[PDB]
Image: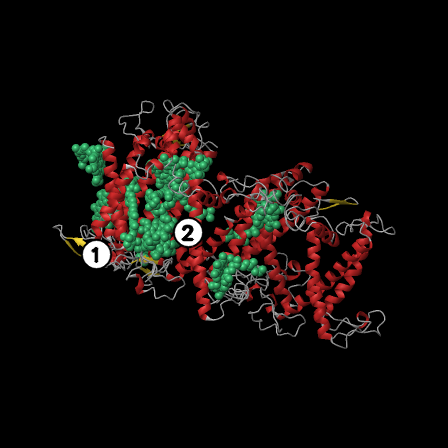
């Protein structure tokens, strides 16, 4: 077949000997510095992988593993934000009174008089009023606790370790061949159907089962400690049916094409929630379901290994 | 690990370590001896 | 090839030399050409056999308490659905073990760490595990050239499959029962999620009124 | 080694029938080391002989006096009249010293074979040693050896394996149904379908602890369940 | 009762229609692609795949046309539910 | 060939079966350089000897406090000692650092210069401070019984026993620390609590070690 997994086994030795030789990637920098222009060129040419070599296979392998590094770093950054919201935050206080409490997730150490930046943001808390929108995003996801943010941070660190391992693996241990990267049809099929289709479908599911009930109870004045945890909504269909009666019917209306039964949590209200000033999360869930279907059909467009599909 | 310690002896790593050290020393001096406008002790 | 879904591309490397080689490799994962990592044919066959043995232990263990309590041979306290045994405490847990599930889980960690890392070291270095002292047990841990079939004095305890054709037939029976049990475990999970009841309870309810107890009628 | 433990198995190449009761079993390969095989044969003989004595003792103790539980006969308040409520410390001292002597002698016979044969006080008397584990002489006073020794060793080790199994059976039955061997057999014969390993496994009749003249012996069962 | 409904019959009709269109040379299949002008022409199949049918109708074809017919029938059902014709 | 920490895994080339307690355990390759490996060998031996002393002292004082003698726990003995005896903790600490600095600088400058420390500069002591091997000083002062001298196989067996009991005592002191941080009580209080109910009383039933439950 033409679309297949193709890799070189152990192409590059994992060794520190090239860390100790700055400018190894270049033939014009491996000769060592004589001028400082060398010190600048070592950094300008570090990621110009097409000027290190000229064959597309090693370039593509370097690119793939560097993308894995970037993803690991983004995961470190996300885990850091979630952790600072779990440890150095006024988030649990902000849920109870979001209209008066300033979101803050960064506390400053009192060292050189800079504890003045730890301002009176609210919630019996002193810190830097953040502008990232992470509190609103977490309330939309239905967090309602610092423990969930802490465990999201731990998961993000695990995923960062996974990404860095994957970069090391896909460069040093089993690096894909060039013909694997040039499967743009399969790459697009998977990135539309899987990355965006299954991703939007999974987020729609989270919103059906976690975000919508948690935020419907939050908008009903229920204190976040009285709100059922997401797994109690997953397990007990009676609670969800009490919030959204269509859950009493199960997933039968989906398979019987009686989709209008789901108009309780799959809406087209448009506008804004008058309690929060944000979008209706039922509209958002329906949106993500719709674009999930759309991307999943879009990811069946290109021809990979069977006769159906398109050759771009 | 001769090559790893050669890497740690590189200009950027040594600079990072040395300036972390200097900044931490100054920060601890300013924590234990706060607000030193003049040499009076 | 047999097993509809097989392809001329998959039959290029599926010679029929592996147990359960029915040509079904539509995604072409057993192609040895330019395939390393864990998509190596050796590792994939090994993992199929391992998932098979674990899964046909589990396909019997998820059904056995319910069947033995239906027969009245075990008391009703141990007659439980497999997911309310302590494996998924939210779905339910059993209170009457000799220890709490995490003590037993640490015992499991140590035991299975030992066992599975011995297994791994014999996969990575086949000639190993018969070389270092293990309380005399290293005489049965010599294994074979194949990792999924060590077949020493313990792992082949009754020396079954003495000829090559008998061993091949037995490997085929093993992998077929194991694929069946892997599907049975996937079905156990799917039925526990959908119906919320045990696999034997689902079987009984389908055998009583099949037209009104099926995957379609259980969507509600 | 002929007529092995299973119809289709092969004997390991270190079990060739030179030991008595050799069915070539060794599925864990523990006897692959000859040193360990010698030591394990000695431990097999020890467990076998002590278990033959043990089943004989439990049986004859239930037959002579069924008044007393063998699981509780070690308690000092259940001891015969010349020894009732005896101090278990001095008793344990007697046993400890008198068994340390003989077991260290046996162990030195294992280490240096044929070095502790002579009496150490009256140095005119030497126990023989045809094999390690079979001293003879004062230990074979009736002289049943110097005849078919291999056949008698086979009989010994077979009855000893059986007695090991049987004594662990006694212990587990006493832990499950709280009865002795013959008591359990008669309780089975009384109702051989409502009194068996079913409806009796899962319940341990052994207490959580037992006070013995001040000490508290922890008193476990061999499996979990019901106190 | 769903079996016998208008929805059920619409769906089975759509799926069988797409399956019969592909099997009998009225829809692109694994073995027959279309050109820029929609004329069915033999494809290269990119793997080669075995089927004992007289027409080379794969289970990949059954999957493709079941998905196409399910989309068709879903759209038809929900559009007749939309205009009130169901 | 030789027992390895991870059976099947070949040992690294820098860990030949020559040092005591050599099981080929160097996943981070920290002792790949020979001089660094000598330094780490002496570090392991010093750590393990201090940890053997510490485990023995903690165990003995815990036995004494458990049977009822006048003993505090290891986490309370410093305060009890400096307050029962009117001992100035600064004075004690600087005396300790003076003496241990003398001793450990002698150590350091015998490591840097093995031929050193035996010139007779200290008090005329020449051969009492020359050192037999790296980490094994020996002599009439550090080995008064002469157990390194005489039987060599016994000396190698003793080196193995020393390094292994030292690693075990390091693990034991780490365990004392973690057990105080978790259970908040002494080591033999922990042991008695475990021997009381081995199940339901272990690290899985503190809520500290396993926070899942
Ligand atoms: C997906 C994003 C992406 C990717 C993968 C690349 C990748 C690449 N670019 Mg492109 N580029 C991008 C985005 C991207 N770029 C954007 C957004 C711009 C506009 C700014 C450019 C503009 C650009 C130019 C103009 C050039 C490249 C070049 C390159 C190549 C080498 C770059 C290198 O070695 O720098 C290594 C990294 C550095 C030297 C670090 C730069 C640090 C910046 C200047 C400071 C900013 C840091 C921070 C945000 C500020 C606060 C810092 C604090 C300490 C004060 C490489 C193929 C070069 C090339 O191909 O040469 C032939 C080249 O000439 N890129
Ligand atoms: C984008 C990533 C990111 C960024 C910018 C920060 C930034 C910061 N963190 Mg956070 N952190 C992150 C990720 C991040 N963190 C992650 C992933 C974790 C989990 C491992 C943490 C766990 C963490 C803790 C536990 C603490 C911080 C603290 C801090 C502050 C001082 C750190 C310091 O002095 O370094 C020192 C660096 C060297 C000595 C070198 C600073 C605002 C501290 C803080 O805010 O105290 C009030 C603090 O106590 N961070
Ligand atoms: C310890 C593990 C390890 C080791 C020994 C090596 C060893 C090697 N790698 Mg591999 N690699 C690893 C892990 C490892 N890699 C991982 C985890 C990845 C995934 C990202 C890769 C991806 C990778 C690629 C894609 C390439 C290598 C290359 C190399 C060679 C030299 C690299 C070099 O000069 O390093 C020294 C370089 C660094 C120390 C830079 C690290 C930068 C990190 C990843 C990002 C940090 C960003 C930071 C947060 C920014 C802060 C900004 C600041 C202002 C705050 C050498 C054989 C190169 C080669 O030519 O091999 C033949 C090559 O092209 N490796
Ligand atoms: C990816 C997205 C996603 C996910 C994961 C879920 C998941 C779930 N939904 Mg939701 N849902 C979604 C999207 C999603 N939904 C969307 C888009 C809609 C709008 C149409 C809905 C509308 C909806 C309604 C209206 C209802 C649900 C319900 C449910 C639950 C019942 C699942 C069920 O019956 O299906 C069956 C699923 C399976 C049979 C798969 C289980 C397979 C298991 C995991 C196999 C593993 C076995 C393993 C191999 C062996 C054991 C392992 C080990 C122990 C040995 C479940 C929690 C119902 C419920 O009860 O909610 C509380 C309900 O009433 N959903
Ligand atoms: C951009 C992401 C990316 C991409 C494109 C690849 C691509 C590849 N990887 Mg790499 N890999 C990645 C990330 C990625 N990997 C990460 C993050 C890890 C660390 C966890 C690895 C670890 C890894 C190993 C160890 C191996 C590969 C292998 C492969 C090859 C075949 C994989 C395949 O088809 O199996 C199909 C995929 C599976 C069988 C995985 C199913 C199980 C996973 C956990 C589920 C997928 C995650 C899902 C999207 C999100 C969770 C869903 C869940 C909640 C339901 C191919 C070159 C193999 C190879 O041939 O070597 C190159 C191989 O041995 N990869
Ligand atoms: C029906 C399922 C099945 C089948 C056909 C096989 C078949 C085979 N296995 Mg696999 N295996 C299975 C399940 C199965 N196994 C499971 C669940 C496990 C995990 C516990 C294993 C673990 C395993 C290992 C580790 C090894 C094998 C080996 C073998 C081969 C040797 C012959 C054999 O096992 O007897 C044929 C099987 C049967 C007749 C099945 C009978 C099923 C009954 C219920 C079992 C008897 C129960 C009884 C109480 C067992 C204890 C006896 C005694 C101690 C009291 C053969 C290919 C060995 C091999 O390939 O060496 C060359 C080998 O090394 N298998
Ligand atoms: C003969 C059967 C049949 C019938 C009666 C209907 C009837 C309907 N369809 Mg359905 N449909 C069918 C077959 C059918 N469809 C099939 C076979 C498919 C698969 C391709 C679809 C896929 C489909 C989708 C995806 C959608 C509909 C929608 C609709 C409704 C309004 C469409 C409209 O006026 O948009 C008017 C739109 C414009 C004038 C311009 C739109 C421009 C876009 C936004 C920018 C590009 C209407 C009830 C819509 C719906 O359900 O909304 C309630 C909708 O979104 N249909
Ligand atoms: C010297 C060995 C030793 C011994 C005999 C004990 C004995 C005991 N411990 Mg302690 N403990 C030890 C080491 C030891 N511990 C170490 C090293 C730690 C730190 C991880 C702890 C932390 C600890 C806690 C937090 C608790 C106990 C408790 C207990 C008691 C019950 C057992 C238990 O909960 O499991 C604990 C058993 C272990 C942690 C395993 C033993 C040590 C392993 C084998 C060390 C392995 C190191 C490995 C070889 C190399 C590491 C590097 C590697 C990761 C790359 C029991 C008296 C509990 C108690 O107080 O009982 C009431 C309790 O709550 N222990
Ligand atoms: C936030 C975050 C995090 C977490 C995350 C998560 C948690 C995620 C999840 C995710 C998920 C959890 C996902 C899931 C998914 C699922 C899916 C995607 C499903 C699908 C399904 C389907 C597609 C179906 C199909 C079908 C049907 C419909 C019926 C039957 C047949 C079939 C099967 C074909 C972390 C830690 C990382 C850190 C960072 C951030
Ligand atoms: C054997 C045979 C036969 C018969 C056969 C048959 C009967 C078959 C069937 C087949 C079938 C019966 C198939 C089916 C398929 C289906 C499918 C494949 C489905 C799919 C689905 C989907 C894909 C979905 C999608 C979606 C959703 C989910 C939502 C909405 C949107 C959309 C639509 C996208 C004959 C002729 C006789 C002869 C010989 C051979
Ligand atoms: C393939 C895509 C899905 C992948 C798997 C999805 C992850 C599911 C995680 C486990 C969730 C367990 O919960 C899921 O099964 C339970 C058992 O029937 C259902 O529980 C429901 O049925 C039970 C039995 O009648 C009753 O307690 C209630 O009616 C109700 O609680 C939940 O309504 C459902 O959400």
Q: Is residue F137 left or right of residue C28?
A: right
Q: Which residue is mark 2?
A: C183
Disc 1 on helix, strand or loop? loop
Give percent across and percent down for residue E39. 13, 52
Give percent across and percent down for residue F151. 65, 68
Label 1 resides on the chain identified as E
Q: Nearer the viewer, residue D197 or F159?
A: D197
Rounded to the nearest whole Å, what is the CA distance between mark 2 and mark 1? 31 Å
Relative to E59, say whether D147 is above or below: below
Disc 2 on helix, strand or loop? helix
Q: Nearer the viewer, residue D136 or F31?
A: D136
Give percent across and percent down for residue A217. 40, 26
Relative to D110, say whether C218 is above or below: above
Give percent across and percent down for residue A95. 40, 27
Q: Residue furthest bottom?
A: D147
**What's the residue at 39%, 34% (across, down)?**
A210
Q: Is residue F199 left or right of residue E72?
A: right
Q: Which mark is residue E31?
A: 1
Q: Is residue A110 left or right of residue D20?
A: left
Q: Quadrant of residue D26?
A: bottom right
């Amino acid at each position: 077949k033409k679309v297949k997994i193709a890799v070189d086994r152990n192409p590059v030795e994992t060794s520190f000997e090239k860390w100790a030789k700055p400018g190894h990637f270049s033939r014009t920098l491996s000769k060592g510095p004589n001028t400082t222009t060398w010190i600048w060129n070592l950094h300008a040419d570090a990621h110009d992988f097409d000027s290190h070599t000229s064959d597309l296979e090693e370039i593509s392998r370097k690119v793939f593993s560097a993308h894995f590094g970037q993803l690991g770093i983004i995961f470190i950054w996300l885990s850091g934000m979630y952790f600072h919201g779990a440890r150095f935050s006024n988030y649990e206080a902000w849920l109870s009174d979001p209209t008066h409490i300033k979101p803050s997730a960064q506390v400053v150490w009192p060292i050189v008089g800079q504890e003045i930046l730890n301002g009176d943001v609210g919630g019996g808390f002193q810190g830097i009023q953040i502008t990232s929108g992470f509190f609103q995003l977490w309330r939309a996801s239905g967090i309602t606790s610092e423990l969930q943010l802490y465990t999201t941070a731990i998961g993000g660190l695990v995923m960062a370790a996974a990404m860095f391992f994957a970069g090391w693996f896909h460069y040093h241990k089993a690096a894909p061949k060039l013909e694997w990267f040039q499967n743009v049809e399969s790459m697009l099929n998977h990135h539309l159907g899987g990355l965006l289709g299954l991703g939007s479908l999974a987020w729609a599911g989270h919103q059906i089962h976690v975000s919508l009930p948690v935020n419907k109870l939050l908008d009903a004045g229920v204190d976040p400690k009285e709100i059922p945890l997401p797994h109690d909504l997953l397990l007990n269909r009676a609670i969800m049916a009490d919030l959204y009666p269509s859950f009493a019917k199960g997933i039968a209306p989906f398979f019987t094409l009686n989709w209008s039964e789901y108009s309780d949590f799959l809406t087209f209200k448009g506008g804004l929630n008058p309690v929060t000033g944000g979008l209706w999360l039922s509209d958002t869930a329906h949106h993500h379901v719709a674009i999930a279907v759309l991307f999943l059909v879009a990811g069946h467009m290109y021809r990979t290994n069977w006769g159906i599909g398109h050759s771009m | 690990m001769k090559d790893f310690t050669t890497y740690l002896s590189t200009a950027p790593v040594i600079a990072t370590i040395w300036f972390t050290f200097t900044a931490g020393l100054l920060i601890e001096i300013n924590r234990y001896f706060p607000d030193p406008l003049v040499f009076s002790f | 090839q047999l097993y509809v879904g097989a392809s001329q591309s998959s039959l290029a490397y599926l010679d029929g030399s592996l147990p359960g080689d029915f040509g079904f490799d539509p995604l072409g994962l057993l192609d040895p050409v330019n395939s390393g990592g864990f998509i190596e044919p050796k590792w994939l066959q090994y993992s199929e056999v391992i998932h098979a043995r674990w899964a046909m232990l589990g396909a019997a263990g998820c059904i056995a308490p319910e069947v033995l309590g239906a027969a009245g041979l075990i008391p009703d306290a141990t007659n439980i659905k497999w997911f309310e045994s302590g494996v998924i405490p939210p779905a339910g847990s059993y209170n009457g073990y000799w220890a709490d599930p995490y003590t037993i889980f640490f015992v499991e960690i140590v035991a299975m760490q030992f066992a599975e890392l011995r297994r791994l070291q014999d996969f990575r270095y086949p000639g190993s595990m018969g070389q270092q002292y293990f309380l005399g047990l290293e005489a049965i841990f010599k294994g074979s050239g194949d990792a999924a079939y060590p077949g020493g004095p313990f792992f082949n305890l009754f020396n079954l499959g003495k000829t090559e054709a008998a061993m091949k037939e037995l490997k085929l029976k093993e992998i077929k029962n194991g694929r069946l049990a892997m599907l049975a475990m996937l079905g156990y999970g799917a039925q526990a999620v959908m119906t919320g009841k045990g696999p034997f309870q689902n079987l009984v309810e389908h055998l009583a009124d099949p037209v009104n107890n099926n995957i379609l009628t259980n969507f509600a | 080694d002929r007529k092995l433990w299973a119809p289709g198995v092969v004997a390991p190449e270190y079990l060739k029938g030179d030991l008595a009761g050799d069915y070539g079993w060794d599925p864990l390969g523990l006897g692959a080391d000859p040193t360990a095989l010698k030591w394990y044969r000695q431990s097999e003989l020890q467990h076998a002989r002590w278990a033959m004595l043990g089943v004989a003792g439990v049986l004859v103790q239930e037959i002579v006096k069924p008044d007393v539980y063998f699981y509780e006969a070690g308690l000092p308040q259940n001891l015969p009249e010349p020894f009732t409520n005896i101090n278990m410390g001095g008793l344990l001292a007697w046993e400890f010293i008198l068994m340390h002597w003989v077991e260290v002698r046996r162990w030195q016979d294992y280490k240096n074979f044929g070095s502790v044969n002579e009496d150490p006080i009256f140095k005119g008397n030497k126990v023989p040693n045809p094999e390690m584990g079979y001293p003879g002489g004062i230990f074979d006073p009736f002289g049943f050896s110097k005849g078919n020794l291999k056949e008698l060793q086979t009989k010994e080790i077979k009855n000893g394996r059986l007695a090991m199994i049987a004594y662990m059976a006694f212990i587990l039955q006493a832990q499950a149904t709280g009865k002795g061997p013959l008591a359990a057999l008669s309780a089975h014969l009384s109702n051989p379908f409502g009194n068996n390993i079913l409806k009796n496994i899962g319940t341990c009749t052994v207490p959580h602890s037992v006070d013995v003249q001040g000490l508290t012996i922890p008193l476990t069962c061999l499996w979990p369940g019901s106190q | 009762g769903f079996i016998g409904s208008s929805t059920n019959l619409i769906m089975v009709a759509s799926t069988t229609a797409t399956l019969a269109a592909a099997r009998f040379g009225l829809a692109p299949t694994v073995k027959k692609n279309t050109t820029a002008g929609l004329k069915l022409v033999d494809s290269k199949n990119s793997a080669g795949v075995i089927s004992n049918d007289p027409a080379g109708f794969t289970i990949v074809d059954v999957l493709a046309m079941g998905a196409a017919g399910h989309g068709l029938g879903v759209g038809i059902v929900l559009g007749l539910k939309g205009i009130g014709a169901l | 060939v030789r027992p390895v920490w991870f059976p099947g895994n070949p040992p690294p080339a820098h860990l030949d079966g020559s040092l005591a307690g050599d099981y080929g355990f160097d996943p981070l390759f920290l002792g790949q350089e020979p001089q660094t490996l000598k330094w780490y060998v002496q570090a392991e031996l010093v750590h393990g000897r201090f940890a053997m002393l510490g485990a023995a002292g903690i165990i003995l004082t815990s036995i004494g406090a458990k049977v009822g003698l006048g003993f505090p726990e290891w986490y309370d003995a410093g305060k009890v000692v400096v307050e029962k005896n009117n001992i100035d903790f600064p004075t004690l600490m600087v005396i300790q650092f003076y003496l241990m600095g003398w001793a450990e600088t002698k150590r350091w400058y015998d490591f840097k210069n093995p031929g050193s420390q035996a010139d007779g500069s200290f008090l005329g002591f020449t051969e009492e401070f020359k050192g037999l091997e790296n980490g094994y000083p020996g002599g009439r002062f550090f080995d008064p019984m002469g157990l390194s001298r005489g039987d060599a196989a016994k000396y190698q067996e003793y080196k193995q026993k020393e390094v292994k009991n030292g690693r075990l005592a390091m693990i034991a002191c780490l365990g004392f620390a973690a057990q105080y941080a978790a259970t908040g009580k002494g080591p033999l209080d922990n042991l008695a609590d475990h021997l009381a109910d081995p199940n339901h009383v272990n690290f899985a039933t503190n809520g500290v070690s396993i926070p899942i439950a």
